[PDB]
Amino acid sequence: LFPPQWICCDIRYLDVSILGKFAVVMADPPWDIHPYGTLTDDEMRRLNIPVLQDDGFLFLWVTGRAMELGRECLNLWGYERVDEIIWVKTNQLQRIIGHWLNHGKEHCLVGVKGNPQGFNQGLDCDVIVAEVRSTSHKPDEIYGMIERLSPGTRKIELFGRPHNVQPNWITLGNQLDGIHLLDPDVVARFKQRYPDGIISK
Amino acid sequence: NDYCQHFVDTGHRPQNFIRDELIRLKDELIAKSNTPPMYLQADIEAFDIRELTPKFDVILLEPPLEEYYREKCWTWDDIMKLEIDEIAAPRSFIFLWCGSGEGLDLGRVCLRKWGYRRCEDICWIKTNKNNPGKTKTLDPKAVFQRTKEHCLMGIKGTVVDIDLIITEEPEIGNIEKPVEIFHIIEHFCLGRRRLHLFGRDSTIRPGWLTVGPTLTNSNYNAETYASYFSAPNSYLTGCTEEIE
Ligand SMILES: CC1(C)CCN(Cc2ccc(C(=O)NC[C@]3(O)CCCN(c4cc(NCc5ccccc5)ncn4)C3)cc2)CC1
Image 1: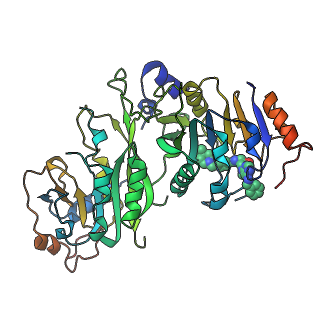
Image 2: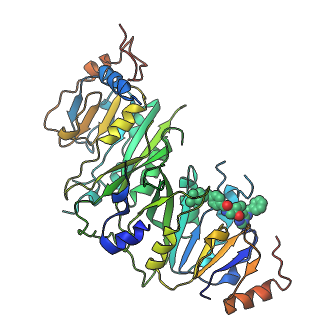
Image 3: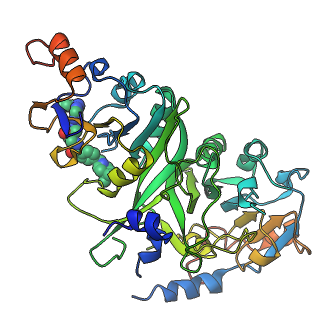
């Protein structure tokens, strides 16, 4: 269970019912806002997010018109938006790095489903100040806030890249290197669902 | 390194560690172009908004939300029922202070209801350099300490600064928003008919019509106000020289 796990896959076609239930879901979708790997608005609506959690939180990165489309998806999938994290993007000297204003931040919606119990709400605040890395690399600080919020629990990241794999997390994305599963329950259900190790439409 | 961890360790918000050409000739033009300040005490709930003429190029809307008071507020029920589309010009802009809770969603519902699309999300980030100790009382639904507020910008019709304002968190019971929002708005050069709904004596500003329930005095006259924009000044941006 505990060490990093991941599945190289097309998230549109993976049967996510094999993965079980998660205290936290995080997604950084390739929204159709203006690209290879883009999902249309309908594909995002149809993602089977609802099977992934009974009680917990969803972290959904949004930009441009996905500020509104992500809210639509959040509600369609069964969540209520209860917070919004902004990451203020800095250089190495802590200076700050949409056609009306220059953009100093990225947004991450925070949704809740059910009635999560035993989370450490209010330990962190809703502003991240962290350095920009490569194009579209989210700050690692978010994993720390999520771990302090829900220590030790199972988490799943959608549309992650190899540098996103973390202990306690299962990472899904089509640029990951193969399949690396260690949780025996997930291994069992994966082999039954995918006896030949292939994930097709 | 990790300012989030540092906030957990010390109570200093991450924004406490953010560090900081001639855009002043433009500010001078804005100043020469501005109309006299005009202002009207009005109970907006009981007020027929349509008596405010002419149609506005820019509307700044600052309804007093209950969440601003941790020491008469407007609910999003009340705010949604305002008839803002009846006074907005067919090409115009709106800046709606939404707070940090359900207003981030219901403010977007309002924008769409009045015929706008959101084109920017302006975040007022509050530092706590002078009170690292003072923790926050959390809204029941909140997952994190809320240390910012959002002002949504919307556009209707056909068609510099950063989308961040950073200031120290005001004293408790001070509901005032950073004056920097006016600077951002005026630097867009969107026209000269500018309305600030739920403004106060303390926010009255050249170039703006201020309408609100707590104003102590009024000088608004619809005919006088319209005369500021009659030919040849009808389509000035507020960033150009006055017409001789
Ligand atoms: C700064 C931010 C916080 C971070 C960046 N964000 C935007 C963002 C940009 C890039 C990636 C990224 O690189 N993510 C890895 C990927 O592999 C990339 C490719 C599609 N992607 C898929 C796509 C998929 N099915 C769809 C599909 C469609 C056509 C052909 C094949 C597959 N299934 C699994 N993963 C996932 C992620 C987010 C902004 C804010």
